Image (cartoon, coloured by chain):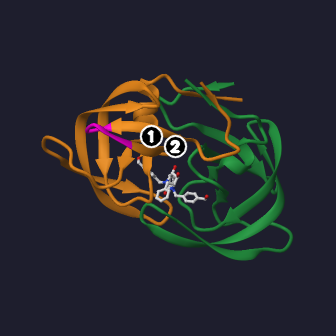
Chain colours: A orange, B green
Amino acid sequence: PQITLWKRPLVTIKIGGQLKEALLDTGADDTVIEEMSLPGRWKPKMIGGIGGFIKVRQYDQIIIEIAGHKAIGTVLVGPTPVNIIARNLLTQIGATLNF
Amino acid sequence: PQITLWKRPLVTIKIGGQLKEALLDTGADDTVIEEMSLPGRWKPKMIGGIGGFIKVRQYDQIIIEIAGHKAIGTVLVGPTPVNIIARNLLTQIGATLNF
Ligand SMILES: O=C1N(Cc2ccc(CO)cc2)[C@H](Cc2ccccc2)[C@H](O)[C@@H](O)[C@@H](Cc2ccccc2)N1Cc1ccc(CO)cc1
C-alpha cells in the first residue's frame, strides 16, 4: 500500500504466533520489540536514541510477518512503549519513502 | 524522489538561514533540531525515547526547507544527537511510505 503520515503509521505484526501492533519507523536502524520470549541465543547490543544509549538483546533470523508481508531478520528486545519496525525489515518488504 | 532504506534517509534542510543534515523519521510525531537560536516565543517540553527524556524548547510556525520543499510547523529545539524531520512536516511535503 501507500501510507500517509497524518496518523502514526501503525500496522499489525505477527511474531511467535502472536499478533501485535507496531510502528513503521524510518529513523530507526534495527527493529525493536517489547519484551517477549524469542528462540535461540542472543547477543548484546548498544542502541542510541534521543536521551542516550541503552543495552538491548539482539536475536538473529527471527521470523516475522509485517502487515501481511513475510520477513526474517534481526529483532532487538528492550524497553519501549511500542514495537518499532525499522529499516532492516522495512527494506526486506520493499518499503520506500516517496515525496 | 524515492528514498530506499538500505541506509539512513539523510537529507539537507535549511532552517533559520542555516543548512543542516537531518533524518527523515516516520516514527516521530514532532520535528526535533539540535540546539540553535530561533526567533519568536517558545515553551518548555519534555520528549522521551530510547535512553530517556530530554528538555526541549517548542517553537511554533517555523519554516523549514526540506530537500527543496518548503514546509511550516512546530519545531522542538534541544540536545538531540541527530536532527529529526518528523511526521508534522513530512506530511506537508507530501511524503508517503509505500510497499
Ligand atoms: O529515540 C528515538 N529513536 C531512537 C532509535 C534509534 C535506534 C533504534 C534501533 O536501531 C530504535 C530507535 C528514533 C529517532 C532517533 C534516531 C537517531 C538518534 C536519536 C533518535 C526513532 O526513529 C523515533 O521513532 C523514536 C523511537 C522511540 C519512541 C518512543 C520511545 C522510545 C523509542 N525516538 C524518540 C523520539 C521521541 C519523540 C520525538 C519527537 O516527536 C523524536 C524522537
Q: CA distance from mark 2 to mark 1?
A: 5 Å
Q: Which residue is mark 2?
A: A25
Q: Is residue B10 magenta?
A: no
Mark 1 Cα within 10 Å, few/some/many (few <14, many 20+)?
many
Local secondary structure at mark 1: loop
Residue B14 lies, in percent from the top left, at 77, 48
The reply to whether dot 2 and dot 1 touch (C-beta < 8 Å) is: yes
The one of A34 and B21 positioned closer to us in this rendering: A34
Local secondary structure at mark 2: loop
Residue B62 lies, in percent from the top left, at 82, 58
Q: Which residue is mark 1?
A: A86
Residue A82's place in the image compared with B80, above or below, is: above
Q: Respond yes or no on whether mark 2 lies under 8 Å from ligand 1.
A: yes
**Chain containing the residue with disc 1:** A
Determine if residue B72 is in view. yes
Residue at 56% across / 62% down in the picture?
Answer: B80
Residue at 60% across / 47% down in the picture?
Answer: A8
Amino acid type, callout 2: Asp
Amino acid type, callout 1: Ala
Residue B13's place in the image compared with A98, above or below, is: below
**Chain containing the residue with disc 2:** A
Residue B13 lies, in percent from the top left, at 72, 45
Mark 2 Cα within 10 Å, few/some/many (few <14, many 20+)?
many
The one of A60 and B17 positioned closer to us in this rendering: A60
Q: Quadrant of residue B31?
A: bottom right
Q: Is residue A18 magenta?
A: yes
Residue at 71% across / 44% down in the picture?
Answer: A6
Residues in magenta?
A15-19
Quadrant placement of the C terminus of chain B = top right
Residue at 42% across / 24% down in the picture?
Answer: A69
Q: Respond yes or no on whether mark 1 lies under 8 Å from ligand 1.
A: yes
Magenta stretch, main secondary structure class: strand
